[PDB]
Image (cartoon, rainbow, N blue to C red):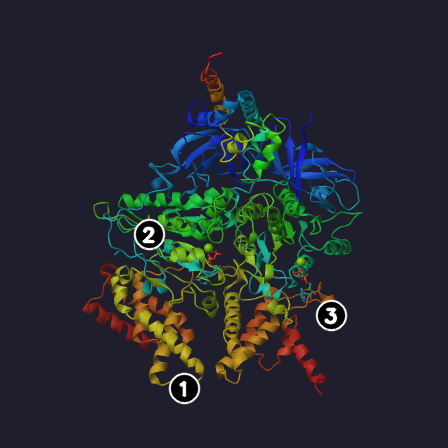
Amino acid sequence: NLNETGRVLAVGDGIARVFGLNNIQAEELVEFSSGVKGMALNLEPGQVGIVLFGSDRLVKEGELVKRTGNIVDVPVGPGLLGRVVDALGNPIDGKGPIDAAGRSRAQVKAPGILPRRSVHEPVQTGLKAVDALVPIGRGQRELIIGDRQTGKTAVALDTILNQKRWNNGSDESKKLYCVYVAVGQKRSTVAQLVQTLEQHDAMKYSIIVAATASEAAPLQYLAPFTAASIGEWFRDNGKHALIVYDDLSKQAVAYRQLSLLLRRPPGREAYPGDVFYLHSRLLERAAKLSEKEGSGSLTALPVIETQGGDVSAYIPTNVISITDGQIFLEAELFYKGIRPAINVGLSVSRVGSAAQVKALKQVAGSLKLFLAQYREVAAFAQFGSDLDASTKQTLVRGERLTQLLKQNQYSPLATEEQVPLIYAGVNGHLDGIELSRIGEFESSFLSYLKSNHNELLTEIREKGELSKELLASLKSATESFVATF
Amino acid sequence: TPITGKVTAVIGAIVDVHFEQSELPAILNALEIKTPQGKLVLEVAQHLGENTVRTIAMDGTEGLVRGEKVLDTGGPISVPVGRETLGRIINVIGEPIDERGPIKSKLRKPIHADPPSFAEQSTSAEILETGIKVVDLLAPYARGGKIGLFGGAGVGKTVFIQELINNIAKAHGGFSVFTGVGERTREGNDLYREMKETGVINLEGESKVALVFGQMNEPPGARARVALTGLTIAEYFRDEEGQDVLLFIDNIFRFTQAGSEVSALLGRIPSAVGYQPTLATDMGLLQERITTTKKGSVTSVQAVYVPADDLTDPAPATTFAHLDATTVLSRGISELGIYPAVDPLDSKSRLLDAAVVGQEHYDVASKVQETLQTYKSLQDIIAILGMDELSEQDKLTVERARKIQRFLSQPFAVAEVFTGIPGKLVRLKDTVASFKAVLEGKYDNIPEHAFYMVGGIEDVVAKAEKLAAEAN
Amino acid sequence: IYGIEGRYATALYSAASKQNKLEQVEKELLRVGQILKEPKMAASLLNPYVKRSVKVKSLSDMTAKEKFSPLTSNLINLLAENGRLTNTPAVISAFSTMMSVHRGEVPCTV
Ligand SMILES: Nc1ncnc2c1ncn2[C@@H]1O[C@H](COP(=O)(O)OP(=O)(O)OP(=O)(O)O)[C@@H](O)[C@H]1O
Ligand SMILES: Nc1ncnc2c1ncn2[C@@H]1O[C@H](COP(=O)(O)OP(=O)(O)O)[C@@H](O)[C@H]1O
Ligand SMILES: [Mg+2]
Ligand SMILES: [Mg+2]
């Protein structure tokens, strides 16, 4: 009798100890008489611990409980494109049922060691500071760690917007579909975000998964995992996907809540022992597949929220260890006028130049190393002592390179527009220009090439590299413009 | 037949009720107990099992005897809603506490209700002029948006709000709902005086605002529900009436503070810092209800308390994410004598964009930040060496910076009894031009003192001239 | 009926049989069954809030005012020593079959 059903013994705080259910599986979905569904996480002889996806004011002692017989899964396929679903994969935008092609589980095994490929495919983020210093690669997971109100989401958001350059195209192997995963955010914000995507015709290749704070803790916990399965889909069918988690810091808080309430002993700061295993079996799910598998791939941009700039924290360290580098963002640099406030000193990419564009690779070789020297000289000129020709020369250029990296939000720049700017920087053609001039210089120089030397922009774009001839013309195009005005 | 039960345990603000009948009341329901003093209201929290339930007292549990009879209400704590609540002081329970007779309202909705659907969410980018320099210039508030006023103890969170009510509630045109959660009972009374004198609340006439109080003197159960009571009233005018409403809350922190006192007795495993595991959710369900929908707009000014001046504290740290505008007060600034002690650096808003406040406004603001920032980054040097060691360029930025900081201060009409200086209301238009003029270096001759507690930019030059005659 | 659980009574009443307390151990054991059916008891016989040696004391109150005390003032602590007060009713049943085998397992010469 009780094999497929059970009576509730206690209920509260989204937890429900039901009695019976001696044939239910681990992590299996269930349904109460009230209509509200739940998830079984603790299997014990006496009772079964279940977590509620909705309010608990509806469940009461002695209520009937039924099982689903299936592990919590979510609808997947192209249909979701442009739609906004919740943890479970149900539509929340109000635009009809989700037309899915298949259904995959929440928890999926990470791709094999055999079916992998070294990351070689770039991920144009449109951010010069990024594509030049810490390039992204199809199949890696680049962290975006920083304090509140710095510009973490910004970096991610602009990326999706930049993809419009190829998603409107015909070629598939070049496009890059985007999966935003809002977790812990308020519905107000999510609404405004999705509004902004549409204002840029970026919603058509974008899938959004909402797990606002108001929803139940188990939703916020499951949100990322289900969302990942959504993206994995493209990876398997030989397409490219780009998922953004924002943010795992909240997810751990959520997952911490189920543990404590299920009366599971806490580790450090109340987080469950396996809190690491929470993000490890998530990020590893994204990687570059073998040619046999489809040459498919899934890129990940995890987001973390530090307190007081303390990266030595419990959760952040757990994730820094997994991610293929991190884009550290400091509040202090933001006010100084460095926007986006990317600290090069601490931001790195483990894939490195392999992922970066070949063209942009040439124009900026030791650029990151040079910016390191700049901060070295910038700190030493604090003494208030005169500087020779060497220490002032690099100080002049290093100060302007930092000003060239500043780029406005919602303004992704193609590759053909980044190369030229960086070119004139690393060489030293901006040294002879005032700092408050670098601003308009960028826009003016671009308009110059798009009008006159447009042929070059077309070669850099297609070729993606720099030939002996292309450098010659590019060289002369730069000097000619400096002379102007 | 009324459902009845007996008490089995009484620990603090937590009473365990048991029902002989096989029908148990759901969660979030109310209960009442007969006493010589009146009636004690209970609220279901969780079903411990064995036809026993755990509930949270709404008032003192002194005198409660084990096995005493308990009557069921049949519905979650409800409170009267409608224009009938205006000009009346409602209690956490939903009963008049101003001694002016019962609130004859038409309908009575429960304090517990689910947050607006994602599709119902409506976003807006309209600016809201307050008159406050440090705000309308740096982090302007938005119409029907969420406002937050963080800060330690005695930094200026209430006094800041009082001014907002003296400048917006008057020229508003809609309705207002003030709810004092865990605050000095005295401030409530004096607040009542102000509403009467200003005429916002006329006993004989009509009123424009409703007063709901769950002061700190009240036990934890109340300090936990009061916020919900006040909110239910305001969401009525939002959907039912579909009219602009100003929701003033102070202080919102008490909401989680009051819940962390009982979480222990409820049998929950304390999370780090002592706060209950479900901090994120509870705080979530509250903020998600306080928002603008497609039926009406609501501007909320919530004040948040900062324990031990720690912004990393889980309580306030989970509040920022639920705000479209954040104005943090650092006691390190108030002690300087600068008021309001707004910290330009930490302060953020969503309206700080050139596509809204204008290109010039964006540039002027940014310049102010950079200047203030450069002063902070050299602060270490100043205490050690001094300005003598500062470079020519750096030394000029400091003075200018120090001028901008002092200029940020603004005399408050509400705080005139503290500063002894008549209030000063400055328009956004003049404020921008003002700082912009200071950036251009058109006032580097005027002494810094002339920027301290000054209203309009004209008043600076005026005050500078007055100091010439005082010099002997 | 099974064996291990049924042996509990037979391994406690075994000594009882030598005396003939089967009545004081079989009639008492019947109490443990009704105590489990008691909803209020379920919140005490299985409450992890008491303790490992505390709840055992409160038992005496149900051992000195129910029927227990002699051949049940040991099985009581044992029944609530590890937490076998959930399927204990099955152990009492075996006693009825084991309590009948003791009558035949005796030098019947008289
Ligand atoms: N590139 C940029 N240039 C100028 N301002 C920016 C830039 N990127 C972001 N901002 C500003 O920073 C503010 C917050 O940015 P953002 O949303 O990126 O922070 P966040 O990391 O998402 O913080 P939270 O996680 O709390 O939302 C916004 O008001 C925005 O105007
Ligand atoms: N605009 C202001 N100008 C001067 N003082 C202020 C201002 N705002 C607050 N204060 C100071 O705060 C004190 C009152 O504290 P209050 O604002 O009530 O702190 P809290 O935020 O803890 O309620 C007053 O004595 C006053 O000097
Ligand atoms: Mg964000
Ligand atoms: Mg106050």
Q: Please report the residue visible at 71 percent of the width from the left and 65 percent of the height from the top.
A: B415
* Marks 2 and 3 on same chain: no
- Nearer to us in this view, B449 or A64: A64
Q: Which residue is mark 3?
A: B420
Say the numbered circle drawn on residue A386: 1
Labelled pair 1, 2 in contact (Cβ < 8 Å):
no
Number of the front mark, 2 or 3: 2
Mark 2: amino acid: Thr
**Viewer-nearest residue: B85 or C101:** C101
Corner quadrant of residue B343? bottom right
In-image side of B446 versus A67 (left or right): right
Quarter of the image where the C terminus of chain A is located? bottom left
What type is the residue that disc 3 sits on?
Gly
Amino acid type at image mark 1: Asp
Q: Which residue in the structure is indicated by mark 2?
A: A299
Residue at disc 2, secondary structure: strand
Q: CA distance from mark 2 to mark 3?
A: 61 Å
Q: Secondary structure at mark 1?
A: loop
In the displayed structure, C27 sits above or below A463; it is above
Residue C97 spot, x, y in % from top left: 47, 18
Mark 1 residue's CB less than 8 Å from ligand 1? no
Residue A324 in percent (x, y) is at 33, 57
